[PDB]
Amino acid sequence: EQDQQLVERVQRGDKRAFDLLVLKYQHKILGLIVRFVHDAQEAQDVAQEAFIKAYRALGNFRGDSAFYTWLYRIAINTAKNHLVARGRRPPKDIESPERAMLRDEIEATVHQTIQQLPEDLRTALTLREFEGLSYEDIATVMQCPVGTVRSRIFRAREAIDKALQPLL
Amino acid sequence: SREALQETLSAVMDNEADELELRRVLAACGEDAELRSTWSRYQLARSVMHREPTLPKLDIAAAVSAALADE
Image (cartoon, rainbow over the protein chains, first blue to last red):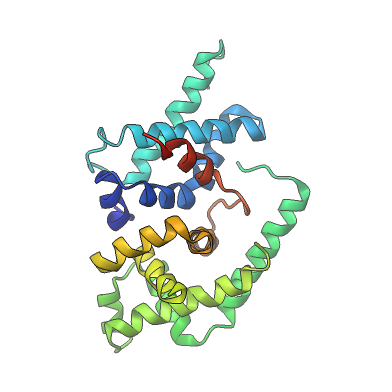
């Protein structure tokens, strides 16, 4: 359960937390819808309906599995149903050339800022992102307080965000 | 408090936020457009570190939030 704190709020019915999961997973859900509808707009309108449907069936989510695995199949279901709604028997992100350049530059700016980070920002931020360690477990590894771990990652994420703000 | 809320956003990303700030940021996200945009960007960059699909300047969330707003 990668989104535990934010899942707890939506299972409690929090729509602002749901706004965060849609904001967080909109690309993956769309990159899935696109596989089925082959229209840029039409997929977004389904992706809407799939998230709208996703909220409405949060009662039927038991926390049995990861929220995204659960949510992903609701998105899958919506799209094939969209095909099944029309006579079509049901069986990646494709952008405007201007957006494929922007995405590349964003990708370039992300990796470049990481490359230029102070080591502690880089080690702490990665230990979270790639080693999957808790702030607790990181504090032990980097021989630092738990409050420092929370700060270093924030600053590391802040450095990347400041580099990307003009791009977005 | 945007900067403090931005640090809170970072902890929520890692599920290390305290229960009180968790309540606080979700309310601030509702009424500070830049704060939600910060979350959007944070997860946008997070997908790059993990090489996941990204489509910059995509905001399906707003149309969903609006559609879920009432009821």
